Image (spheres, coloured by chain):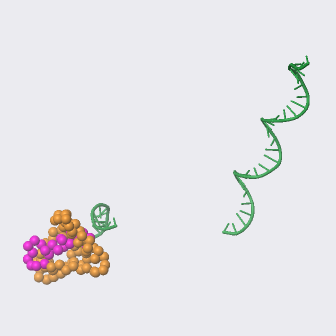
Chain colours: A orange, B green
DNA sequence: GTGGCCGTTTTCTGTCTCGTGCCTGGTGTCTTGGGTGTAATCC
């Protein structure tokens, strides 16, 4: 994927992929389905947002409004707050 | 390219009987009195 001008897109199923695979070639990212682990998505974004990435990277989240996606996304935001007030400011 | 297992995400009238309890008829065991009995003592 990195060393070929063709082979533009490829699906990854971000459970198996994210162990540290180097995919700096990517610049755009599409998230299709929200996951349960709030962590599995940071490695997913890091599949194109490696340290010192060559070009700007963007994330497009898919979210079905008025569905379980709403509950999961709010849950993930709450989980981010959990690790973002325990380690940032316990007054939040 | 074969699978093993763990790891993971969330919070039926009808009639009868069997038994017995209660009512009743009998029956025990007794208490009172009433007379019979003895006492007895006036004179």
Q: Is residue A36 magenta?
A: yes
| In front of the other: A90 or A77 | A90
Q: Percent from the top left, x then y, of residue A77?
A: 23, 72
Q: Percent from the top left, x then y, of residue A37?
A: 24, 69
A5 to A16, vertically: above or below: below
| In front of the other: B12 or B3 | B12
Q: Is residue A5 magenta?
A: no
| In front of the other: B20 or B23 | B23
- How many marks the image carries: the answer is 0
Quadrant of the image for the C terminus of chain A? bottom left
Q: Percent from the top left, x then y, of residue A1?
A: 14, 78
Q: Quadrant of residue A54?
A: bottom left
Q: Main secondary structure of the magenta part?
A: loop
Q: Percent from the top left, x then y, of residue B34?
A: 88, 34
Residue range in magenta is A35-57
Which residue is found at the position 29% from the left and 74% from the top?
A71
Please say whether residue A22 is visible from this viewpoint: yes
Q: Quadrant of residue A35?
A: bottom left
Which residue is found at the position 17% from the left and 74% from the top?
A45
Please say whether residue A15 is visible from this viewpoint: no
Which residue is found at the position 10% from the left and 71% from the top?
A51
Q: Quadrant of residue B10?
A: bottom left
Which residue is found at the position 16% from the left and 65% from the top?
A88
- Residue A1 is left or right of residue B3, and the answer is left
């Amino acid at each position: 994927f990195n060393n070929d001008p063709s082979y533009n897109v490829f699906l990854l199923t971000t459970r198996v992929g994210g162990l540290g695979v180097n995919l700096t070639g990517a610049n755009r990212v599409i998230i299709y389905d929200p996951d349960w682990n709030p962590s599995t998505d940071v490695q997913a974004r890091e599949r194109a947002w490696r340290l010192g990435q060559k070009k700007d990277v963007t994330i497009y989240r898919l979210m079905i409004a008025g569905s379980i996606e709403e509950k999961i996304y709010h849950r993930q935001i709450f989980k981010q707050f959990l690790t973002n007030k325990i380690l940032k400011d316990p007054k939040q």
